[PDB]
Image (cartoon, rainbow, N blue to C red; front, side):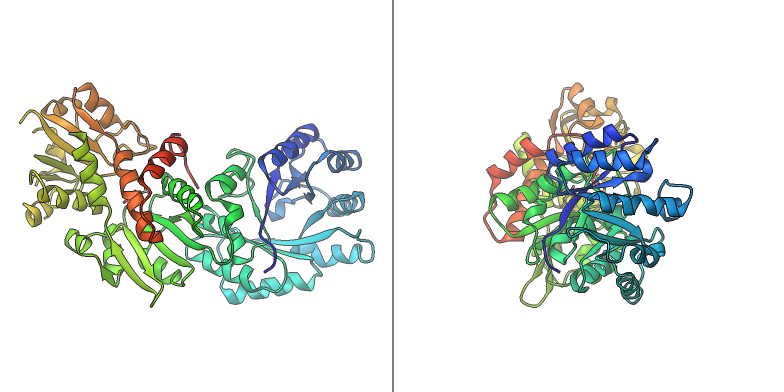
Length: 498
Ligand SMILES: O=C(O)C1=C[C@@H](O)[C@@H](O)[C@H](O)C1
């Protein structure tokens, strides 16, 4: 429905003068409007403070005076609360937000008294779940019947599949609709508004000033997710994982897509259940995915066709949806990225026997030295299907060999977790850690103190990523670009996108 989505910045400073500065920062960062959260002001003088904000804000203003019974801070008399919103209207507000619960009464109170530019948002907040399309439809119709100018519905993501229902609502409701799904599993709903008809999304001045769970920053919407480039035809890609908030795949693929003017967007996909995820997002809108822990093996099963390298590895880390028939094709770029990063570093000990361990184990037997796996669960086979070692024993273990961590051990926030004792590294000449967040794991740090050769996970991450770009876009992998993107935009640590 109609225009690209606006970016609204929530303004929650507890004093009038600080809110003024926040509206200025909102303007500097690129926000399109501000939501003035009046219920967050510590000492409020409505006529005075309202006049101040409207006079000084460089951006159009949306006033919200959220009561405690709708998730806000305001307590006290209800008519006084409404008096303030009407006051904001007659003082020159661009919008007010009024709760569905009181919306009929309130809109009646201003009938024939609205200024010309003024729109009334009527909102409903669901902190439990995301209702069925049938129940959302009825919600939309109820909000319309109050006389709302704009419909606002926030729901809660119990599973990421919930987001498809909200997209269906914003895409097809014939009324300007703000439709958002809260929580980390709902984050995709906040990014893709301009493709699915959303009127507005909330982006924060920074990650500390969140007004409801899941909101990204304005800067990430604009510069990381390329918000202004997203449109109805943009194809959606993403990193399927659990956890997923550490992933820098959205940073690199969005920069590459933008650099080559490819009409795609890459988001985080926090997926609990891989089967239901793929079923829920089967349309052509969702053109490909990357697959991380713990879904690499299940993805191989969910794919209709499987590349031989991935077939014979047992795991899929890249899913392409073929436009012809909607068919899911599965590839593996972990092998080449891992092995080639190690070869450039210069008997193989592979920590972990999940999808990433399978790809590295497979690759190593293919070229140079075919050797031994170590997993938490000892009995992870793979040392047989390729040519084992219980995790508790791996420290107790040649002088100048190799070791390759492919588990999540050491990944943020577990920065002091390491898969093996420092003293046991004396037996190793190269240590590779697929973990790239942080860049310097405890394992890699201690491995270097042990005088060994350290190849970081970023060497593997960038390599496997430009191979996925090639699969995703059908365009030649722009290797130099991806290194340059990772160097300039993927260097900061302790980043959580959630
Ligand atoms: O962190 C990430 O985004 C990923 C890491 C690796 O598992 C890759 O196999 C996956 O494709 C992307």
